[PDB]
Image (cartoon, rainbow, N blue to C red; front, side):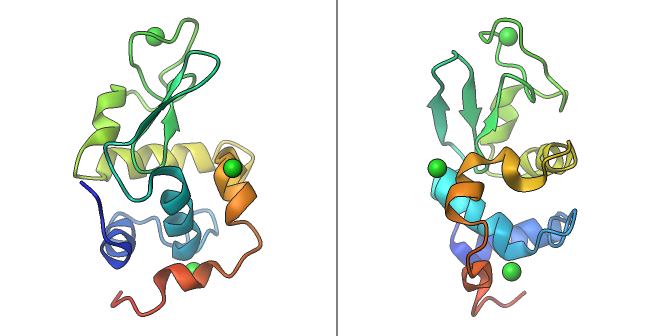
Length: 129
Ligand SMILES: [Cl-]
Ligand SMILES: [Cl-]
Ligand SMILES: [Cl-]
């Protein structure tokens, strides 16, 4: 599913991501924009052999099981395929664990490089939320 910008903002808020660990909704929408362009089916293969899955490009080295990332963990206790669903529940619940892991949203390198310090509220501007 490719979400609309405000549609995704609403879904994220529905699932309790808004201001989670102090990160406003615009931060999460911005991260999703640059990780996946709002496409739940996004996948990307990393140099280390792990893969990133879903709207927030969650990585199989630590967070989910895909059966093909040697020496990895599955800390969200989910198959990586669950992160590709039109229903963002699994991605949101896993993101909550990731952002609580110590480095906040810096876990998403694209958030650090493209969202951090910017006017992230622009991402939810105009949205009925
Ligand atoms: Cl915001
Ligand atoms: Cl594996
Ligand atoms: Cl980047």
